[PDB]
Image (cartoon, rainbow over all chains, first blue to last red; front, top):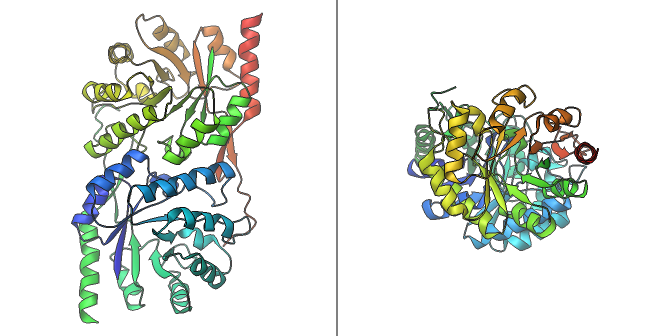
Length: 235
Length: 234
């Protein structure tokens, strides 16, 4: 299985790379669940990270029913990420009823060109999982990040397995709560790609008193990669 | 006094403008306290908003003691905002002892060029307010956003009035808790500029499920502008 690490900085992305990560999902604002990184961060990652990096395109937290103004920015960000040379990107747009907004997604796919597009956890808030998978396949989505529509991927494992079994659908990447302690569950289930934040808290260096920084734990990345390699060796 | 409204989207910035805002501080991620907006949002604003807009340059929430990696991004963001034609920007970097990081701020000023740089609430985390004002003046900082080093600007208004008396310092802009109900207090105090995030969390329009978006209150912006005008009129 491929190991994707969610990173909130260039340094974290580099740490993930040096510890075995196969891919990185690049975001900003962990308290928002991941927002589009600024151009400064995007350019920095393009110059410092060599493994595949897929930036998230999300202007704000909350739902995925974007206004025309927000969507205009999303389209520009897609074009920009493509122009900068990223191999893929992560995004997702839904209508008020939880259906994938096809017109909006088609516009995103057009702007993305040849990039490998990941439809993110908006999938976990959508109605009709199988029908949605079919629509995502129609759009040409490369993979879908999902927790099986549950609080965490492990709880939604049965769902995830149903998604993988579903014919004519993009790659299913398990995400949300995935860590070394439960990774084997997904590997045995046949999950081809896993997403983890390998999160850890870093104390603030401030002496005069700002809070802890959310960062990637290199040891955790290496540990998960070892688990995948050993599992890949047995079967 | 000049009215600056903190907006978290292009549409909110336009709403602020249409209701009398003199300037907009453009941010993303309200839950993080305001982070750098993506290029798409930046370009959108330059295309639609005419009043002065100062984007915030802040890679993450929390403290202002950025890593070398984060700082590299910050400088590129400063160059980007300058190249896009914004008239100013908002940022701030501190050391571990609560002092302005002069060596790094100097690099920011260099990259900023002619843009009017606002030092944000990192100011309220500094050990010595007066010495910090001197440092900001030394850097060429245009203005500083402060709550008088208190939970809210009203609580720190006596301190703000003291700071305003200090010559050769950046413009003092009161911020944190500023609203129509208490604006008259800052105006009477003689504050030259006020910063308000006049808005609220609007519920998501989603009708399906297996407080979602922070929007500006255009009516509040209009009300505050009226208060400012009437205060100056008679």
